[PDB]
Amino acid sequence: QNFITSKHNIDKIMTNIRLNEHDNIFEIGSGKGHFTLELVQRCNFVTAIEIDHKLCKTTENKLVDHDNFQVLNKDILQFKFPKNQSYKIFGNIPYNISTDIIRKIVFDSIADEIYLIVEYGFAKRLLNTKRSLALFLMAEVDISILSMVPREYFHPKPKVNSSLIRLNRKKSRISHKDKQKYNYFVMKWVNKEYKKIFTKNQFNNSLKHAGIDDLNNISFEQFLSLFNSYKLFNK
Image (cartoon, rainbow, N blue to C red):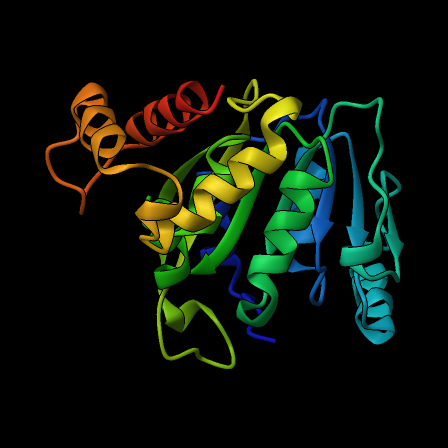
């Protein structure tokens, strides 16, 4: 629900999306095909993943004059993305499953660049180093809010505005080796269960060592410093 159908608005949004003629794209949710139509004209090939079969049909009808696409009536959460292919993602996604979609495409796909339209508050949370999802994502991708999408652009009109965000894949900051240890550290840190990860002395030394003077506001680099100190203290 909450589709964007004004061509005028669609163009303004596409203006911030820098996908090119040679990129293969996976669209999360096709809606009635309003963005799908733009993507196929802009990009090399588009694979739209849509759970609702009627929408798949509508999208298909809207793109009748295009050949560089396919619509798959599947569940994004169960979809298996390519493993030896360069591709990007775009998605005007539902708030209710935003968290699951993003973990799915960031942790279970190798898309090197992802463009998503999410609620304004959700987007802000993804950059908040006090939250676990943000800390897990920042180890795999860089995140940036590109523009604000007014709720008037949607229908039904949501009660809050949205944001167009971009996630860029980068070399993981956490080795596959420190996976479990990182997951534990993140959770205990966001829950402020400091005692389970640092003795009082290690805690203070780690903070000064990371240059953190205000616990209520730490950069991701500072958090990584903390995780590194955590590793050192524990063999």
